[PDB]
Amino acid sequence: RRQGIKKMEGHYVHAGNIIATQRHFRWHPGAHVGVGKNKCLYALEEGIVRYTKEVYVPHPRNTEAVDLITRLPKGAVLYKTFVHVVPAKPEGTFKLVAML
Amino acid sequence: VENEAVAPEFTNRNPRNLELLSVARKERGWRTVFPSREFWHRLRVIRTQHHVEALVEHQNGKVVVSASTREWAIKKHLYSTRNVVACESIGRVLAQRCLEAGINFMVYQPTPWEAASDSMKRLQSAMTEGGVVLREPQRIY
Amino acid sequence: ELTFEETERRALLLKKWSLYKQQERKMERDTIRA
Amino acid sequence: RRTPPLGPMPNSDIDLSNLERLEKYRSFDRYRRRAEQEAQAPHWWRTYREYFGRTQQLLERKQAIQELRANVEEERAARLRTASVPLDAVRAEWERTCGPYHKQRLAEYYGLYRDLFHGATFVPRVPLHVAYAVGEDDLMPVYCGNEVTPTEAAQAPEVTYEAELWTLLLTSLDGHLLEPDAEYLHWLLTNIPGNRVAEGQVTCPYLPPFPARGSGIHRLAFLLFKQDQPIDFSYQLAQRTFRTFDFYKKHQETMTPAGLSFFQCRWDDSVTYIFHQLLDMREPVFEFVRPPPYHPKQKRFPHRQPLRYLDRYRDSHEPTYGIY
Amino acid sequence: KNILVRMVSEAGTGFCFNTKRNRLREKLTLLHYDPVVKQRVLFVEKKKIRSL
RNA sequence: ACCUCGGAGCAGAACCCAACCUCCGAGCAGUACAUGCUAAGACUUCACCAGUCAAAGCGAACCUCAAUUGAUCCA
RNA sequence: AGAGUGUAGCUUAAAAGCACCCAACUUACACUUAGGAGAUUCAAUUGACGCUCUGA
Ligand SMILES: Nc1nc2c(ncn2[C@@H]2O[C@H](COP(=O)(O)OP(=O)(O)OP(=O)(O)O)[C@@H](O)[C@H]2O)c(=O)[nH]1
Ligand SMILES: [Mg+2]
């Protein structure tokens, strides 16, 4: 299957690069990280890849996750591993084109 | 002419420059988590036991324009601060404040039950009739 | 069909029962704890 | 091997064998609130934030609220969800009570403090009001973060504020054309007697906004300083450029900021007129240029790549014939 | 089982696309996007291509 | 009995690797008919063949999950 | 008689958040939506009005 992480933390990533391939949701998409049909994590921006742990708030439509989280103790909070792309370059710059 | 000495690259430091030009990035990930971060400004409503509060908050987390019924200036004009009237009034106040602050476009991320709520519908109607549009323009790539 | 006055009276009835049964539950809980 | 946690692991305090007796999240909203609180709370592990970061008045309020509740009409309207609120009265009351704090948050969000005072902050105590007279029948206001066109800002605005001297100043925080940090002053009245503004000392004459075309949206700030005692101070960009930071450093002893009001200006034909008629210079036009698209180093044998691979690296689209 | 059938554009163009329908089910009429006309148009089952 | 494909023993934790063996399954079905066209950048069963994900754009609306398959020639 | 003293039930909350109740959906609960009530004991940090403990 040759699945797993393709870009570890601190690796420069260009937009569109596949960061990690997985069967289940081992790593969750973070900021500027998109998910393919097969749960592949790819970079939506050009920048550095960072792995963090963040509170997991499932979408309300996700019935299984909502049931799991409602069956949870009043103080517990779920955490998941997320992958983020810290964009490096700015969107662009304003350049003098003509002195009308 | 000295007055014509212009740097080849301009540097606009206004935080909302690219956001208003519709060119700034939005956090497009977080597909498996709720709410989505793909916005520039978000309308967040907190309905406490006694007070109803609304916030217009930037993606970075900075609160830009808040309207809380806890404030005297607003609670001194309505009977109950935890009802549909309170929601509608606070929405209208937030719409006015957003217009005066220059925030015309916004993203609202309600839960299914929140959206079905009549009070939330009234608040959204108040915002849209006040001028704030609860749908941000698409990014320009 | 119905009128406005009966609706107002019904709302006042709901308010007054809310108060009354709130006091009832409060006294029940007080007796419990005591 | 297992390295022990560097702090209290989440969900560890409540970890108990009495799960059945432990109250649970009966709803999604309560868990959402708890998760938001946890996300706000700092943590010892890597997190997304690390990388992407009187008594009489109370009595009077209680009495007024009691009177409002006692008013049956108010209760009937509330229960029929048909009541409204006086927007103007609410606006005035908010301005008096807690408008300065919200205006401070707006200024911080727009970066005025970081760009004007290098992060040093304050609160606009004075409920300042500025309005640019459009035509004669009306005057567009200038709130905190408003939006006004240079055409509407062509002439100097009317300023009103219930207070008692004052120094009013207008800067373009990002209108500078050569040095990124500097900014242009548009008009500066000093030693204002009370409320009347026509008696102010015009140290620098009035200029309208001139944001270059395609240069984005420029933020213009009206600053108002309370002034203890007057001090003597001091169409050319070289002299309109300065820094509010050191300017206010030179006068902070007797001047203290107490009012702010800022708006956003775009390009306009009035900007063309400003650049040509009086600035007497060719107006600069700026275009937002994105970086060139990234392509990997071209390979001799682009195995499995489509025919478009070569086009990705060719520069001229027209046919070329080499030596022939 | 299911059969592969050739839905043909009713817009007069020669456009066609293959779909799957149960053999026992009635012949198929279906809105589908027509690239030649650049518009959604009706398509009608013409002939059974194969049985699958 | 088996020959192709998926899952477990099975690599204790990036990937790949325990063949032979113990087994359990697949050679589909359901929905839909934009399940349309295009296109940066990437993954890839250790070759190739083949197989995957996909920003942006045009045009529209406002796939599903283990495998579920077969090249060239030729009809 | 002495000590601790003191925000509606709880709050190293400062007039807020949790709590709490009914109306509808539930057999029911729960969820959700609509609504409901609520306090800083009295006078100038201090004294005295109410509660708990120590005694007769
Ligand atoms: N693609 C394809 N080619 C086929 C198929 N059946 C036969 N062929 C072609 O024909 C060859 C096999 O020949 P045959 O075994 O005689 O085929 P058959 O259909 O059993 O009998 P004949 O019609 O008499 O040839 C293949 O190698 C192809 O060239 C099929 O199902 N698919
Ligand atoms: Mg390979």
Image (cartoon, coloured by chain):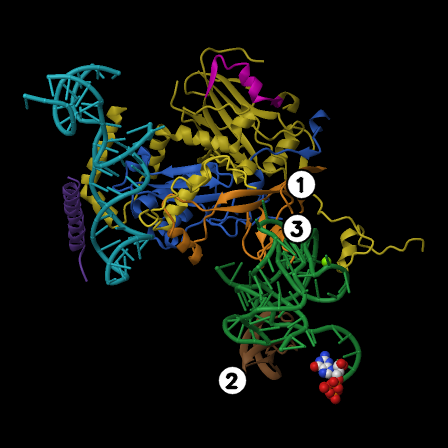
Chain colours: A orange, B blue, C purple, D yellow, E brown, F green, G cyan
Q: Establish whether labels 1 and 2 are both on one chain.
A: no
In-front residue for pair B2/C10: C10
Q: Tell if the residue under mark 1 belongs to the same chain as the one under mark 3.
A: no
From the viewer's perspective, tell me whether residue B135 is left or right of residue A76. right
For residue B87, side relative to residue A82 (left or right)? left
Quadrant (top left, top right, bottom left, bottom right) of the N terminus of chain D: top right
Q: Nearer the viewer, mark 1 or mark 2?
A: 2
How many other residues sit within 10 Å of disc 3, few (<14), some (14-19) or many (≥20)?
some
Q: Secondary structure at mark 2?
A: loop
Q: Which residue is mark 2?
A: E24
Q: CA distance from mark 2 to mark 3?
A: 47 Å
Q: Nearer the viewer, residue G3 or D135?
A: G3
Closer to the camera: disc 1 or disc 3? Answer: 3
Distance in Å between CA atoms under marks 1 and 3: 29 Å
- Vertical order, D51 against D57 (above or below): below
Q: Amino acid at mark 2?
A: Leu
Q: In the drawing, what numbered circle is on residue D287?
A: 1
Query: Farthest residue toward the right?
Result: D324
**B88 to the left or right of A62:** left
As for residue D244 lying within the magenta part, the answer is yes
The quadrant of the rendering that contains the C terminus of chain D is bottom right
Q: Is residue B126 visible?
A: no
Q: Secondary structure at mark 1?
A: strand
The residue stretch that appears in magenta: D240-257
Q: Residues within 10 Å of mark 2 (few under 14, many from 20)?
A: few
Chain letter of disc 2? E
Does mark 3's beta carbon lie closer than 8 Å to ligand 2?
no
The disc placed on residue A17 is 3
Position of residue A43 measured from the top left corner of the image (x, y, whole percent): 62, 49
